[PDB]
Length: 149
Ligand SMILES: [Ca+2]
Ligand SMILES: [Ca+2]
Ligand SMILES: [Ca+2]
Image: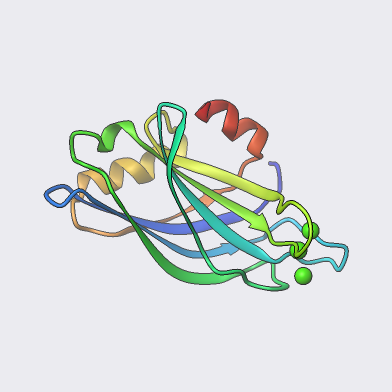
């Protein structure tokens, strides 16, 4: 009920290759982050383990929209012996030309995930090589970061 918006992405894991693929599909219902009434959203993806940010990716920026479509794919190298102990963090931010780009909200999937986040990750693991798309509710960074730290 924090009213930040939602993000849709797919997950795919290939155990033999250790290839983890995340496709950022779209976000909707995003919080307004600029005085014009809109936002300029882009998405960051972090691969994490044990409180440490290991790798990062980011999408292009969409201007002046609360319902951006991306369709941008990213891949990480995670060995099968480690895939159950990592997190994938997905953050939507508002781009501002000057000043800190503030997060709208974020979610993570993987180790220590719960609810729909755990469901998505478990679905990915249960179906090697198969891409699984799912919606997630964005959550305030204060709360998500406390779980990741
Ligand atoms: Ca702003
Ligand atoms: Ca703008
Ligand atoms: Ca902006």
